[PDB]
Image (cartoon, each protein chain N blue to C red):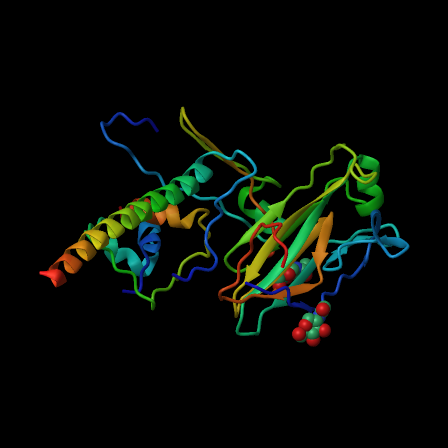
Length: 160
Length: 54
Length: 53
Length: 57
Ligand SMILES: *[C@@H]1O[C@H](CO)[C@@H](O)[C@H](O)[C@H]1NC(C)=O
Ligand SMILES: *[C@@H]1O[C@H](CO)[C@@H](O)[C@H](O)[C@H]1NC(C)=O
């Protein structure tokens, strides 16, 4: 596609806390996260069933990057999402992706036993994006504008 | 359904994915269904998604 | 005509005319459309290939 | 010969079927172009030697 052009969209996440951060991903002095992803957690004592739709009224393809969180303990799972088992479903009119999070203790990286799995979804013009989450959703903040052309990638250590 | 012929058979089947829990239970009763189609060399197990899709 | 090979395989009502048909070359048109229950085929291209072959 | 995005040709991990195919495609392409390059300069040089011998005659 040859571009990282990102357009922020108005997702409304009612009933959850947004912009979660982690000390394994510092930005500045404080904790942070991926700038293009939005870590949603419980608000108060509840994590509702999120149900958001984002139509594509443009003449190009939208690329959506999203993820699901894999906690390491049941205590981490409930204290973040209340529900003992999360679920993330991202669908269009022609596709669906349902991911059940795994709760396992993995080897420590940057002090963390937990993990995040990244997925993607392309929305053709006229189609709509639907996100349905019971918990563990790392939501998108927008879409990347997709292009066709002569761009590519290369592995090299040669100086420019 | 055994294959007692000397040729291969192609079977086309499917799984229904309701949109609400009431649609699920009013059709199949069980809160969560399951479809498993198998031969002696394969097994295809599918759990239906109850979701509201576009 | 209005039917894709997968629609005629499944038996979309407006593709009933294609039951038990045979072919050397199946020609799919742009105007084709589905008019039955909304469905999804994981690995759609592979099922289309082996039926068409 | 202008090419842009192509396939991966070096791999850091063992993957199996799909990687065997990507390697096989590129190895097939290289052997065929190598043959073309070898045959071309052979036909060309033979013809160049003939045409310069012909001018003298
Ligand atoms: C990305 O680019 C657009 C247009 O080039 C620009 O208006 C916008 O500020 C940028 N957005 C982000 C999130 O960087
Ligand atoms: C969830 O979103 C889908 C997609 O628009 C909609 O059909 C469905 O009615 C919604 N469900 C609820 C409970 O809002």
